[PDB]
Length: 180
Length: 180
Image (cartoon, rainbow over all chains, first blue to last red; front, side):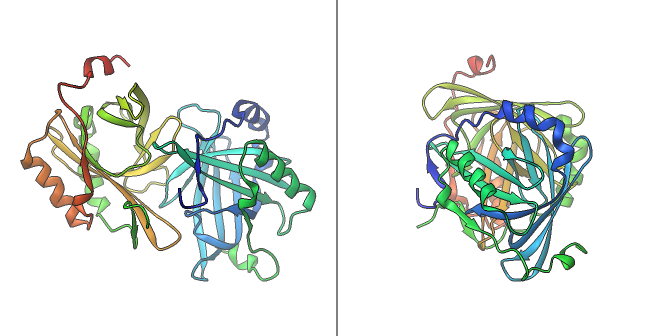
């Protein structure tokens, strides 16, 4: 029970089929660059600051190039993929090199400003861990969009006070990050 | 103050390239039924007792039907897949319906008696989590083979005192399990 990302109870039901209906035809619009505006405590994100995720869609998957400042303060690039769950479940799997793959539900997105992302894993002792993100198309994110994400996470009983803001903005060397 | 499967330092090098080469020509021999003899503390495994994993190989991946008795005392079947890591890394991904996918290394096997399996993940805070397993072609497994896996795990710095025996034997309803 001790870490704040280990939470009583089964992973939430999040109405995946409605979401998959909404999103499948708009995969093309989800490509491009997304900045990680905020996230809940995540022991698997190696990139601490200036997190910049670049998605290319190929018709079957997305290829991701994630860059930013690692926790030791150095530049870091991570290779990712985002593809339909291999068992035919109505969600995607997010898979990164030298890591593992997890379910990734887009709870809500307008494609042009924000996306609200959610992953959950169940334990055999009746608890779960989940990991949530707020993505923006820019370094900052208007309040109105931040509040949309807050509502979508509260709708599935994710405690939104768990979100922490990620360093973004003028202190980030994005232009270097894009060179890889 | 932390779980015994969260260990300081990084995942050790386990020479995957050598294993992968030895193992790609023998996929058909790895198919069939394997019984879980023992494992290290694993908060993801939903089957507690009588763990029986039936593998089928189709020429590109294994399809797995994993059955046994769940923590609640009911029979349980889980559908799983084991396929090459999607980035081209020299290990397999073990994937289960309604779960995540994780790297899985076959540290050692003779195909006809035993297999020693290993999964490890690095965190962002200077620790790793690893998950080890001893598999047998039968419900019991002779000391001769157990010792082989013990040596393999010790060779990669895993503390073998972490292994726990799984209930197997004439008490398990394997013929029911095989039927779903």
